[PDB]
Image (cartoon, rainbow, N blue to C red):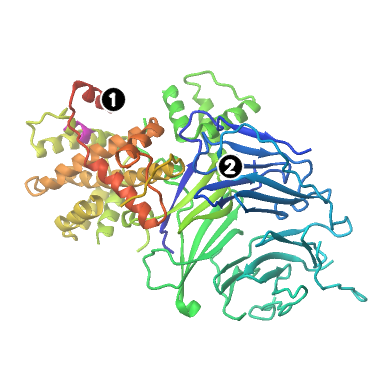
C-alpha cells in the first residue's frame, strides 16, 4: 500500500498576524459541526460552517478569508436534525438556505452573491421566510434534500416523506396491524427525474414522479453477499457507488440497471466514513483505470484519505491508493526531523510562526484558562507545555467533515475550525521516494543514504550543513582544495563517533551503484528543472503554493545534505565529481535560504515568490494536479536559478544576518 499523496495544510488566516478577518458581519434572526465548500456562478469558492447544531451559520470566501468578510447568521432555534435539514444552493445570483427548526418551523435565506463579496457592513431588506407550513410535532423532521428547480424533498423517520412546494405528498400510508423501524439515511438524484434513496437497513428505493412510484425496497443486496444519517452514496454518471455496513466496509457498486459487485475496505481500529466522492481518473502511476473513488475516513480527530482506482469492467481489477495523513510540517515537529530551525524567546517566536496566530492565540487562552503562567525566559517548563497544546489545538482544528473537489480534480478537505482546510496533493517522484522509503535504483541509493544519515544526531547534521554553507560564503578559505575542505569538515563534525559498523554497511552498499549515473539522474533530471492568470489576489491558492514548495525543498534539503555527506566521508575524486559537487553546494545554499525565509515571515516570502512568477503577480490558478505540480516546479526553478552573488554590501549583510 504505497502513499502517493501529501497533505498540505491551509490555515487561511495564517499569513496574517490577526485572526479573524477584519470584517465580520453578524446578522440576527428574530469548535464546529460541519463544513463544506460551495462553487458559485462566478468562479469563486464560498465556505460554510454550522455550529451547535444551529443557531450558527457562517460563510467566507475561500480566496480571501482575511480581507473578505465572513458572514455570521444567528438562529432563533436549532435545526430539527442538525445539518441534515439544510440545503444551500445558488439560484439567481443568490445563496438559498433552508432549514427546519426544533420548533418545526421552515426557514428560507436569501443572500445575494453581491452581499457576501461586497464590503458592505450590513444589508437590509428581508431575508426571513419563516413558515410553519405542512409540518407538525406529529411527524418529526429528519432529512432535507434539494430538488433542481428550487424544489425540495423532506423525509421524516416514519419511513416517509413530504414534498415542499410552499406541501405536496406522495403515496405511502403504511399502517401496521401487526407492527418505528428502519428509516432513510442517504440520497441522490439521477439524471433529472429519479431520486435514489437509502435506508437505515440499508437498501435503496428508486423514484420518478409519478409522485408515489418505485422499482422497490430493493433492500439491495439485502441477500447479496454476506449473510449477517451520513454520506453513504455517490453517483457519477450512470455509475453509482454504495457503501455497506460490514463485516468490513463493503463498498457496493451498482450501475436503468441496478446490478453488480462490491469491493472490500482496508481496516484495523475503528473508522467511520466522513465523506465519499466518485469521479473521473486522476493521473496516477497505474495501468488504465476507468474511475476514481475518493473516500474520507475519520477516527476521532485523525482522518484518513484514500482513493480507489478502478478498471473498465467496472472492476477488471481495483487498486487502493493511500496518502500521508499528516503534513510534512506536522511530521517534522513530532519526529524531531527539522534541522533548519534554531533561547526561549526564540523558541517562542518559532512556534508562533509554525502555527497560525489563530491556533497560537487559542493555545494561549486555554493555557490561561488552566492557570498556567509564564516566568519569561528559562520558563520553558512553560512552553514545553505550550508546544503540546499547539499540536492538540491544530489536530482538533483539522478534524475533517467533508471533501470538496477544487475541480477539476483537486482534493480539498474542509475542517471543523473555520479557515482551516487541507489539500491533498499528488506526489512527484522525489516525494514518493521520501514518503515511502520503506516500500520495496536511485530509490535504493537514496534509501541507503537515509539509512546511514538516520544514525546521526541532529546536532551533527546541523553542524555539517552549516559547514557546507561556509564553503560558499567562502568562510572556508577558497584556496583550500575541495579535498582539504572535506577532510576539515570530517575531523570537526563526524570525527566523533558514529558507529563504525554502520559506515561499513554504507560503503559496501555504495559499491553496488553506478554512482556517477544515479547522481546525474538525481541532479540533472530529478532535482533540477502557460499559466493563468492569476489576476485578483488569492489567497488560498497562495498558501498551497508556498507550503507545497516548502515541502519539496525540505525534501530536497534532506536528500542533498546526505549526498554531500557521502563525499565528506569517502573522498572519491574531487576530480571526477566537481560539477556535481559544485551544484550540490550551490543548491544546498539555496535550499537553506528558502527554508529560512519560510520560517521567518512566510507571508512576505509568498509575495516575493508570487510576484516574480506572476504575470499579474497574484499567482496562477490551479485546475489540474499536473498544473499545480508544474507551478511548484517553476517556483522551484526560480529558486535554484537565483543569483547567489551579492550585489552591494547590503545584499551580503542580509545573507549573513540569516547565516548567523
- The quarter in which the N terminus is drawn is bottom left
Q: Is residue 21 shown left or right of residue 230?
A: left
Q: Is residue 118 shown left or right of residue 317?
A: right
- Towards the viewer: 624 or 657: 624
- Towards the viewer: 488 or 221: 221
Residue to which mark 1 is pinned: 660
**Which mark is first along the chain, 1 or 2?**
2
Distance from Cα at disc 2 to Cα at disc 1: 51 Å
Q: Report helix, strand or loop for mark 1.
A: loop
For residue 223, say whether it is visible.
yes
| Residue 147 location (% of width, % of height) | 68, 62
Image position of 40 with respect to 20: above or below: below
The residue depicted at 40 percent of the width and 49 percent of the height is 621
| Residue 303 location (% of width, % of height) | 55, 53
Residue closest to the far right: 177
The residue depicted at 8 percent of the width and 36 percent of the height is 481
Q: Quadrant of residue 215?
A: bottom right
Residue 470 is covered by the magenta coloring: yes
Q: Is residue 170 shown left or right of residue 632?
A: right
The nearer-to-camera label among 2 and 1 is 2
What span is colored magenta in the figure? 467-471
| Residue 289 location (% of width, % of height) | 43, 72
Q: Is the magenta region chiefly helix, strand or loop?
A: helix
- The quarter in which the C terminus is drawn is top left
Q: Quadrant of residue 51?
A: top right
Residue to which mark 2 is pinned: 114
Amino acid at each position: 500500500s504505497m502513499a502517493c499523496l501529501s497533505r498540505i495544510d491551509a490555515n487561511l488566516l495564517q499569513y496574517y498576524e490577526k485572526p479573524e478577518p477584519n470584517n465580520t458581519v453578524d446578522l440576527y434572526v428574530s469548535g464546529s459541526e460541519y463544513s463544506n465548500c460551495l462553487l458559485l456562478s462566478n468562479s469563486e469558492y464560498i465556505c460554510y460552517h454550522f455550529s451547535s447544531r444551529s443557531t450558527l451559520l457562517t460563510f467566507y470566501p475561500l480566496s480571501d478569508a482575511y480581507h473578505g468578510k465572513t458572514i455570521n447568521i444567528h438562529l432563533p432555534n436549532a435545526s430539527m436534525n442538525q445539518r441534515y435539514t439544510l440545503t444551500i444552493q445558488e439560484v439567481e445570483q443568490q445563496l438559498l438556505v433552508n432549514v427546519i427548526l426544533k420548533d418545526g418551523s421552515f426557514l428560507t435565506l436569501q443572500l445575494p452573491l453581491s452581499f457576501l463579496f461586497s464590503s458592505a457592513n450590513t444589508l437590509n431588506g428581508e431575508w426571513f421566510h419563516l413558515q410553519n407550513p405542512y409540518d407538525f410535532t406529529v411527524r418529526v423532521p429528519h432529512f432535507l434534500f434539494y430538488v433542481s428547480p428550487q424544489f425540495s424533498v423532506v423525509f421524516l423517520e416514519d419511513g416517509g416523506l413530504l414534498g415542499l412546494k410552499k406541501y405536496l405528498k406522495s403515496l405511502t400510508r403504511f399502517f401496521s396491524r401487526s407492527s418505528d423501524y428502519d428509516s432513510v439515511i442517504s440520497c441522490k438524484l439521477f439524471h433529472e427525474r429519479y431520486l435514489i434513496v437509502l435506508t437505515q437497513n440499508c437498501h435503496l428505493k428508486i423514484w420518478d414522479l409519478t409522485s408515489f412510484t418505485l422499482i422497490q425496497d430493493y433492500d439491495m443486496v439485502s441477500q447479496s453477499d454476506s449473510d449477517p444519517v451520513g454520506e453513504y452514496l455517490s453517483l457519477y454518471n450512470n455509475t453509482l457507488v454504495t457503501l455497506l455496513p460490514l463485516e468490513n466496509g463493503l463498498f457496493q457498486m451498482g450501475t436503468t440497471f441496478q446490478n453488480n459487485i462490491p469491493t472490500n475496505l482496508s481496516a484495523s481500529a475503528i473508522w467511520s466514513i466522513v465523506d465519499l466522492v466518485l469521479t473521473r481518473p486522476l493521473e496516477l502511476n497505474v495501468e488504465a483505470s476507468y474511475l476514481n473513488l475518493i473516500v474520507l475516513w475519520k477516527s476521532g480527530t485523525a482522518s484518513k484519505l484514500q482513493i480507489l482506482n478502478v478498471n473498465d469492467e467496472s472492476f477488471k481489477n481495483y487498486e487502493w491508493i493511500e496518502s500521508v495523513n499528516k503534513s510534512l510540517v506536522d511530521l517534522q515537529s513530532e519526529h524531531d526531523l527539522d534541522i533548519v530551525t534554531k533561547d526561549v524567546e526564540r523558541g517562542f517566536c518559532n512556534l508562533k510562526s509554525r502555527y497560525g496566530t489563530q491556533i497560537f492565540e487559542r493555545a494561549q487562552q486555554i493555557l490561561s484558562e488552566n492557570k498556567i503562567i509564564m516566568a519569561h525566559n528559562e520558563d520553558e517548563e512553560y512552553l514545553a507545555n505550550l508546544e503540546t497544546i499547539l499540536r492538540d489545538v491544530k489536530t482538533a482544528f483539522n478534524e475533517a467533515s467533508s471533501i470538496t473537489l477544487y475541480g477539476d480534480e483537486i482534493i480539498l478537505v474542509n475542517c471543523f475550525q473555520p479557515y482551516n482546510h487541507s489539500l491533498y496533493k499528488l506526489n512527484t517522484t522525489v516525494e514518493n521516494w521520501f514518503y515511502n522509503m520503506h516500500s520495496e535504483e536511485l530509490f535504493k541509493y537514496l534509501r541507503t543514504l537515509n539509512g546511514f544519515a538516520s544514525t546521526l544526531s541532529n546536532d551533527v547534521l546541523r553542524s555539517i550543513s552549516k559547514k557546507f554553507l561556509d564553503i560558499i560564503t567562502g568562510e572556508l578559505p577558497d584556496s583550500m582544495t575541495t579535498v582539504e575542505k572535506f577532510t576539515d569538515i570530517f575531523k570537526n563534525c563526524l570525527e566523533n563517533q558514529f558507529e563504525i559498523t554502520n559506515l561499513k554497511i554504507l560503503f559496501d552498499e555504495l559499491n553496488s551503484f553506478d554512482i556517477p549515473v544515479v547522481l546525474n539522474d538525481l541532479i540533472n533530471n530529478q532535482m533540477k528543472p502557460d499559466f493563468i492568470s492569476a489576476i485578483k489576489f488569492d489567497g488560498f491558492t497562495s498558501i498551497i503554493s508556498l507550503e507545497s514548495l516548502h515541502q519539496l525543498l525540505s525534501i530536497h534539503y534532506r536528500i542533498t545534505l546526505q549526498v554531500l555527506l557521502t563525499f565528506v566521508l569517502f573522498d572519491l575524486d574531487t576530480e571526477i565529481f566537481g560539477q556535481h559537487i559544485s551544484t550540490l553546494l550551490d543548491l544546498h545554499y539555496k535550499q537553506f535560504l528558502l527554508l529560512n525565509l519560510y520560517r521567518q515571515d512566510k507571508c512576505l516570502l509568498a509575495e516575493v515568490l508570487l510576484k516574480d512568477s506572476s504575470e499579474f503577480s497574484f499567482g496562477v490558478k490551479f485546475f489540474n494536479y499536473g498544473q499545480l505540480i508544474a507551478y511548484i516546479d517553476s517556483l522551484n526553478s526560480n529558486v535554484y536559478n537565483a543569483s547567489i552573488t551579492e550585489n552591494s554590501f547590503f545584499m551580503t549583510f542580509f545573507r549573513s544576518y540569516i547565516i548567523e
